[PDB]
Amino acid sequence: ATFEIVNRCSYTVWAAASKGDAALDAGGRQLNSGESWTINVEPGTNGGKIWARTDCYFDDSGSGICKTGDCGGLLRCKRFGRPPTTLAEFSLNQYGKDYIDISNIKGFNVPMNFSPTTRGCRGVRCAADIVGQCPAKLKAPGGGCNDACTVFQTSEYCCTTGKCGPTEYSRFFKRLCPDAFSYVLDKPTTVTCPGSSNYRVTFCPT
Image (cartoon, rainbow, N blue to C red; front, side):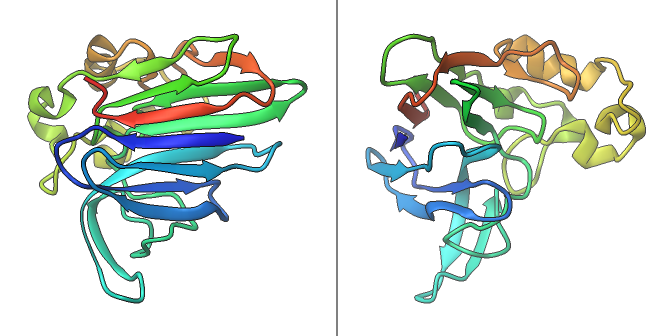
């Protein structure tokens, strides 16, 4: 499957793509404002994620640091990134179907649209000003708006027992972005697409 990753933000981002134990394609790249990066993701990939990283510094060997979404200090991510990160999530070719979503379970850093470029399903978007409106206790100094699990490390926010409810903090994310997951047991906002669809992830879509 092809994913086109487009940075419509006015600032540079460092895109990342991983399935947690491996990079997808090159795993990461700098995207200046307006740039597009096309990656190939193997069919059958389960649990892939794409995200943006902000305020990164990398040396000539591809080692450094980002203020949001850092993946162990690498330009080319092999692992998932440090919150806060708005997440585009996908599992492809699962019994004939692809499943896509946007999640705020690991917080929010950059607004995002995640849409198919082929026929047969709709896209999803979270483009509200979550960082500007972020509750004081969730604000990340580096930028972004953390989720409550990251900040407080409680069973209720992290849904550790498999039983949890919505919270004041999850409802904040949900009010601003109804089409994104706001906590682990949120009513699913997953979209089912035809197997082997292609996609575009746009940072700062509006």
